[PDB]
Amino acid sequence: LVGANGAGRMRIWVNTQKYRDQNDQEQFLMKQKAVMGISSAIEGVRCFGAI
Amino acid sequence: AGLYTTYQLLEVQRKLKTLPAFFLQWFPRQINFQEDMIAFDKVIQDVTRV
Image 1 (cartoon, rainbow over the protein chains, first blue to last red):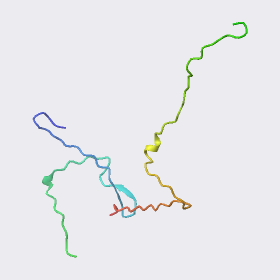
Image 2 (image 1 turned 90 degrees about the vertical axis):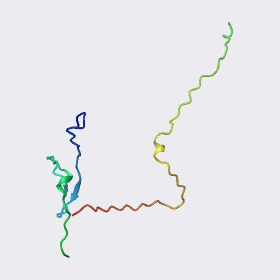
Image 3 (image 1 turned 90 degrees about the horizontal axis):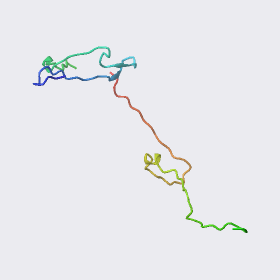
Image 4 (image 1 turned 180 degrees about the vertical axis):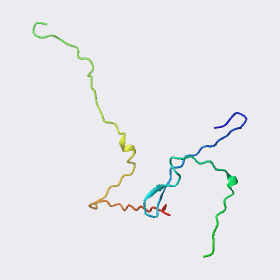
């Protein structure tokens, strides 16, 4: 959803993936009844401790 | 006339119906075999569990 000069450009995705839960139930990876906005500036780090 | 009405036979009007192939487009693989039966092995591996 973008304005002419490129302003305002929300970029839309839909997530419906289901993973197999620990109880073996199948549940949605993304909360289906909700919307998330996120940016690369979350700068998340995948963090691994000592084995 | 009198004994019988004369006629001209004009060309015969044949109507050869057919059932042209539509579904056999999704069955492109042909196997002619003398074994009794055909066998498939189907395998599902869910790899999405946490």
